[PDB]
Image 1 (tube, one colour):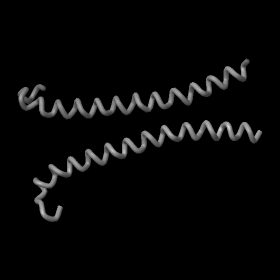
Image 2 (spheres, rainbow over the protein chains, first blue to last red; image 1 turned 90 degrees about the vertical axis):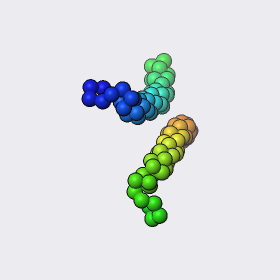
Image 3 (cartoon, each protein chain N blue to C red; image 1 turned 60 degrees about the vertical axis):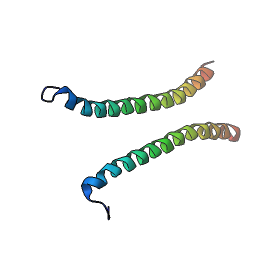
Image 4 (tube, rainbow over the protein chains, first blue to last red; image 1 turned 90 degrees about the horizontal axis):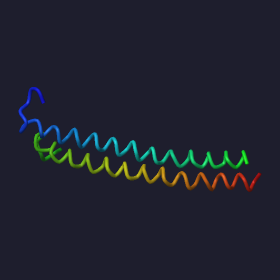
Amino acid sequence: LSRLDPPEAEVQIDRLITGRLQSLQTYVTQQLIRAAEIRASANLAATKMS
Amino acid sequence: LSRLDPPEAEVQIDRLITGRLQSLQTYVTQQLIRAAEIRASANLAATKMS
């Protein structure tokens, strides 16, 4: 942004936005995968407690 | 690579790399989905054995 004019900057900005969107998507997806296998253990724990 | 010069080749190479990355992502994601439903059956099997 400092050493390039906006018509030149936006071409790279599109690329950086694409990459960072993709990496957030991957993180959140795997986070939903993990949540389920922890939930099943919490349910077994509550069963053993009861 | 054989019949095109590198400045021309790289434009297609970017496209092929994008497609193949996407297809590996899809395969590994569904593979983690399957693993969980097999794990639950393995746990029920161990319960029945015990």
